[PDB]
Image (cartoon, rainbow, N blue to C red):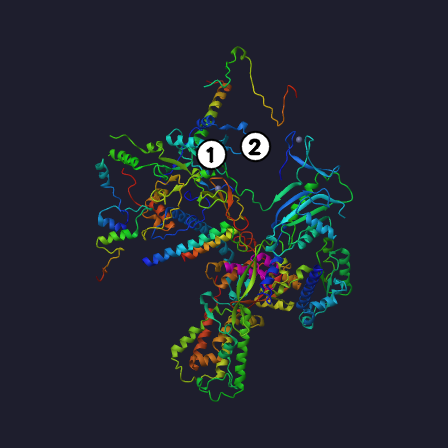
Amino acid sequence: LLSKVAALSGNEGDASPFTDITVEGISKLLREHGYQSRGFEVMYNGHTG
Amino acid sequence: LEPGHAADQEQAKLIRSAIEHTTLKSVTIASEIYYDPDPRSTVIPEDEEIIQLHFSLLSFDQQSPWLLRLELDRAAMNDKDLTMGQVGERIKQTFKNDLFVIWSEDNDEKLIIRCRVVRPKSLDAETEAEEDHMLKKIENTMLENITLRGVENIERVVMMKYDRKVPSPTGEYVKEPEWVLETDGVNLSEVMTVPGIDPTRIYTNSFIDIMEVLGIEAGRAALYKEVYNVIASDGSYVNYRHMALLVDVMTTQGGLTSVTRHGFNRSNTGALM
Amino acid sequence: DGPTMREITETIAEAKKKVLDVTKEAQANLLTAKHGMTLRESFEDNVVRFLNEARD
Amino acid sequence: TNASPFIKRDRMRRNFLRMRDPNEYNEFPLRAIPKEDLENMRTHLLKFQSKKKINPVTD
Amino acid sequence: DQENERNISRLWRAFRTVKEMVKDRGYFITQEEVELPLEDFKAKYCDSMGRPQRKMMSFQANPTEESISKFPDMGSLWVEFCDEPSVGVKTMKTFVIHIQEKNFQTGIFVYQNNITPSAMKLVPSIPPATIETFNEAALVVNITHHELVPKHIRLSSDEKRELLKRYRLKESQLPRIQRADPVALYLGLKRGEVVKIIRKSETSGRYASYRICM
Amino acid sequence: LPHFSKDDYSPESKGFVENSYLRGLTPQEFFFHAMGGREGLIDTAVKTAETGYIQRRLVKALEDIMVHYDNTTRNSLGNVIQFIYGEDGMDAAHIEKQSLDTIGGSDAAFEKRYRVDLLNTDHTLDPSLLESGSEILGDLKLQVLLDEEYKQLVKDRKFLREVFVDGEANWPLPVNIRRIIQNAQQTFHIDHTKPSDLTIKDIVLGVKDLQENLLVLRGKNEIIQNAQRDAVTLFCCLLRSRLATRRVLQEYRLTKQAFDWVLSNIEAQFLRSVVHPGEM
Amino acid sequence: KDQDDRDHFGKKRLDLAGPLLAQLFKTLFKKLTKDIFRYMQRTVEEAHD
Amino acid sequence: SLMSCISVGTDPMPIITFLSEWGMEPLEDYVPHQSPDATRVFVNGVWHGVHRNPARLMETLRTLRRKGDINPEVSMIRDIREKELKIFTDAGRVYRPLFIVEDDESLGHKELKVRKGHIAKLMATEYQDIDVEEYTWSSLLNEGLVEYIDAEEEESILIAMQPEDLEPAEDVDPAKRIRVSHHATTFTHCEIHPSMILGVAASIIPFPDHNQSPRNTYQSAMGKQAMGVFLTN
Amino acid sequence: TTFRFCRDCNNMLYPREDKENNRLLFECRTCSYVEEAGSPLVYRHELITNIGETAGVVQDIGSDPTLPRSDRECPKCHSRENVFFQSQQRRKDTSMVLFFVCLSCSHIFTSDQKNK
Ligand SMILES: [Zn+2]
Ligand SMILES: [Zn+2]
């Protein structure tokens, strides 16, 4: 989830163990980019579409 | 416990105290050596009354002036049902009549035992130097080598209420509670003879003592139960015949043969095997 | 969800308060050791039981 | 909120660089012993180890 | 006087166990005398003072008719209770003579604390008669009544011959049971005697095994 | 840790991780959690080595034990470990857990389920359960046969209770009778309403002679025959309980053709469950 | 007082390349000194240069 | 761990002489029954004497080490309960740096001696290399802002997880982890950063505190078997 | 027990009985020096002991940073600051009773409410 946000924002994710970073904070930023807050996406089967 | 008296919790305490090995060391706070000029008057304010009590109610000429005093805990003698009269006799029977003892009553605020060694008619001039040392010896052995009550090698006993399914008078199986004693340490031969327990159901964790007391076949069943418990402890299930075969092999030679190089590997099955 | 987390936080706090009460009785020596166990061992069993049940 | 999920080091370097008495006593002289008598003479300390009073002058 | 009652109760239980042992060995013992009440025991085997007279406790038993048919070689049995605690050679010597004098094929001796080595070594001295020594503390509880102890049945010479013939075995190929085994002592097994162990199996209900004394 | 004062017994001090993996562990919790995990890793290494030695020792002690053609379990020396494998002569691969219907239940339930009477009207058999339900009432020759069957069932319950003191009824047994009965009902499409053509004599004799064909040992001497009878004691108890006269006619509605099919399968299934000689 | 804990890291020492070489060098130098004396003794006794 | 270091050891004789000149009574005239309050002084496990005022002595020793008069690797432990003062100078002791916490009555509560001004000059020298006076790690050590602490000395200090919450005298986000304040007002040291307890291999895991402990151990071993660029040559 | 030591050579004294007066005397086994006893107690063995519960209390115990602080009331000076610690006995049979040391009067009290 953090890596997805970092690539979309062109930043380096901060994954140090003991920080104030929370999963909810990552989700909010991901939603600002037009993606599902929890990282889920609608996918299509490659065999049938 | 006895099937008729299994649910009687009051009788369980009687059996529990009748098998737990307790020594004077576990029911005492401190032991002191006091010197009294004569065996008729006391120097401690507390025992001023006890001597006046026993002496008035009542040989003492040759009693040694060195006194051994034992202070027992009020709570300790109440955790296990005990009275100073019984323990006083216990000391009196360890050494039949070679020392005099007086014990306070339960109503007393402090529980104290006073002991005096009586010297023989012949006078030993050399023993006066070690007279106190001898008292330090017997008191130590009086703290360790005294069996107030219970079976030796029995550390502690705890009461637990188990559920067993017995047939009901109607004909159905119903769960009734019974009081079961669990013990640390094993003395099967002596405990099995204690009155009040059910000798036809006593079980021991160590199958070795089962074999020595009940026989190889009883050891065979006990060995299987021990193995079954280990297998079933984690919830895993193994077919009976697999464990039965292992147990049968372990007891086929009229005894419990280990699975090490000192057991099955010492038989006569060919050097190459 | 939020409501579940609030309930979870309160549930753990209640268990901690229960542990706090026993830790105060032992300090006052008003706690009787369970039969066959020491005062310290009995206290630890009570604390472990409360915390284990709190997680469950 | 998330206290900055990202390690900002690309421009943070630039930002920091951009930011920049009465005579109520007794006094006696102290003179050294002549060294002419200290030669061929050793002065040691003797300590009697006991709880009582030991005085070779009288005891 | 509590200690006096404790010994009497222990002696009564030990007496009952011995009677059951004699009954199980194939001797004629009625069920009524096996279940003798405690008060009856204190009436017939005690005195005015209360202490029991163990000399009178000794009794004689004879093989039952069914046992004679299966084993037509078993004789009478004598059970003796020693009054003094420390068994000496003197009391041992008269006990063996009392057996050899009246053609007793087996004699069970019950002692309180121990038998001196000078007397123990004399036990195997009157063949073909056999002498078995039992400690009273060991007879207080009948081990055969324990749920873990199955039923042991001694096999006759003919039965042993058939057992080996039908399974085509040898005496060395059967499961072994020690002579010093508590159950074997309870049955007085000898070397070469095979006992049929009938025990309950959870896979077949009833299962029959055989063990040869060694 | 060097972050709490001495004599601190609070959960946060002695290793209570209040957070979840989603929320994250605080540095104190992380170290305490790491300490616990190290215990598991050490145990995994130590357990593997110790258990490996145990397995090798067990295998070497029993490697020479085999089931012989006389059904006895013997080692390389020929010594008999067991006079019949598993005390029943069956193969573990063919055993299934089944319920013993006689041991459990109350006495009233036992009487209602198995007892059949033709003289009195307290436990009578409904005449609509068989084609001969009218002439069956008032027969003494068949009544004694039913009495013997009930007497045997009562004896079985007594024996079973003495074996399983705890009253447990679910035990592993070779043949799954419940499945066989279901197959017969579904295979022949039992009507379940039309009265059956079975007779009381056929059922009692059909079950009785079936027990004779359940042969684990085939010796023609008394000792082996007694052993054969003992080996199928528990299975026969299950067989009698399931194939009871009342249960077959009342609960299963079995037909004579269906009943014969069930008996043949039970004989075939039992013979397939016997341990194969030469198995290690 | 409680018995000393053997696992206490404060009672443990780590020997790095420095101390490890020190003891190794000390042993080797001791051997070198012994060899020097043996040559001196041999030269005096055997009357060599 | 990342910030752990091992002492190389120094000569203990200068410290022994220093202790003697500051009132360390020799052991040849120490009568226990005439001074049952003196603190035993140990140097490298050698009982050199006793002191009547350990509190003043420890203050002098601590100040000298912080200013840079005694080698920072020297470890000093004052066991108040046991009345012992142990000084260790031998090599092989594992130690790590920590911040120093003092009263600083100007603010009324304990706070780190290191301030924002010190950090400002720290980064200035860091970024000027890529000319103000040089300011390196040694400067912090000589200024008494950081201190080397070994395992033995940790037994007599109180450390704070972080300066954000534990040092200041003392709604909450539902997503943040439950942090215990510990309500302690006697902190003597502060952790540089809790994440530094990890080693080289464990410092590559992202969010290792959101993982089950055994998984982190597996990654450490597997991180050493991953293809990469061991060297540029 | 109040061990007594010799006066002439500082050796350990031992109890001796004199029948001339049926009293208690302390004599030296090496230098022949006698001293009349003050108390009739000569040996004391303590199975359950409370000696050492407050061992380690010094005039500067409050200077310890590790020791926790508390807000309990000292019942000799009416103060709120104090440091508390558990018993120093390492036997696994002692209760968790706390011992409080006041930083104003150095008075040691206990939180026990059972026996005190
Ligand atoms: Zn002297
Ligand atoms: Zn105060």
Q: Give the residue at mark 2.
A: H33
* Stretch in magenta: B200-229
x then y, percent, for residue B123: 77, 41
Badge 2 marks a residue whose secondary structure is: helix
The answer to whether H75 appears left or right of B260 in the picture is: left
Q: Ligand 1 quadrant?
A: top right
Using the rendered view, name the quadrant where residue E133 is placed: bottom right
Near-viewer residue (F29 or I64):
I64
Q: CA distance from mark 1 to mark 2?
A: 22 Å
Amino acid at circle 1: Lys
Magenta stretch, main secondary structure class: helix
Counting from the top left corner in percent of width and height, residue H59 is at: 42, 32
Crowd around label 1: few <14 · some 14–19 · many ≥20 (10 Å): many
Residue H49, image x, y percentages: 50, 30
Mark positioned earlier in the residue sequence (1 or 2)? 2
Residue at 48% over, 25% down: G34
Find out whether residue F15 is within the magenta segment: no
Q: Amino acid at mark 2?
A: His
Examine the rendering and report whether any part of residue B96 can be seen.
no
What element does badge 1 sit on? strand
Q: Above or below — where is H93 with respect to B207?
A: above
Residue sitting farthest toward the top:
D36
Mark 1 lies on residue: H86
Does B228 lie within the magenta span?
yes
Q: Is residue B164 left or right of residue I24?
A: left
Mark 1 or 2, closer to the camera: 2
Q: Chain of mark 1?
A: H
Q: Chain of mark 2?
A: H
